[PDB]
Amino acid sequence: IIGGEFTTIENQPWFAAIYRRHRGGSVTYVCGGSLISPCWVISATHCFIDYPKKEDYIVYLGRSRLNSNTQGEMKFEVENLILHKDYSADTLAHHNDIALLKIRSKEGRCAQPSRTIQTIALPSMYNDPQFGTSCEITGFGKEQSTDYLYPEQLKMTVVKLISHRECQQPHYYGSEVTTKMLCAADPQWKTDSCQGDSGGPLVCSLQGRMTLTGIVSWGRGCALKDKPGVYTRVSHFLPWIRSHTK
Ligand SMILES: N=C(N)Nc1ccc(C(=O)O)cc1
Image (cartoon, rainbow, N blue to C red; front, side, top):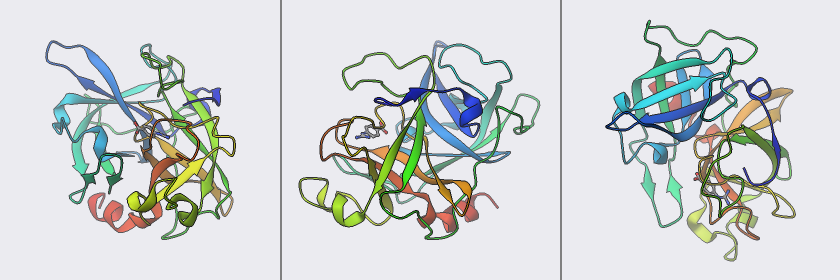
């Protein structure tokens, strides 16, 4: 997250921290995700597509720090890693950039909700906020495009939903943006998602409910003029979500 503010997991208690085991045993952060039910985290296929072996990955819930334990955190193995069969990546764009991780602990339990661990609601079908709505993004991604390190402390910011018409303008992203994606940016381009925020939630208020509207997917640089963040439009994937979590 470029700009915005530091936060703790109690403010975004559906945030999932996804890590990968290396041969040798070093463990590095991969991507964010969102807990949509006690046994299911939703994320981005592009996070896993190079290393699609579920045994390689660890999921934490109730975690506020990247490389240290948060009191109350729960650690899960991935029982299933479901990537979207129609995934494709262009030089920029990721199409159908959505993934489902079925989580289960060493004792074969799912998440127990708490102050630091809660599910986020899915939107109703094709039901997105109006363009110019303010939504929240959460992640451990870079604080600056030129940073080598990720922040140790979770961050969140606010960006405004951009209309498809605006986002498909040539000097923005042209046809690289589709109706299955949402664009969001700061009017001053001063805050954005960045590398390492992939898979993380875009949350908006819909009929008085915090709702998972989007999943961090792609973008040209971060917090660049005319280069919005691009998000998987979750309200266009409910059949795929429903089918693979039955
Ligand atoms: N918000 C942007 N302008 N860019 C941007 C978005 C996502 C990612 C990612 O790694 O998923 C990287 C860069």
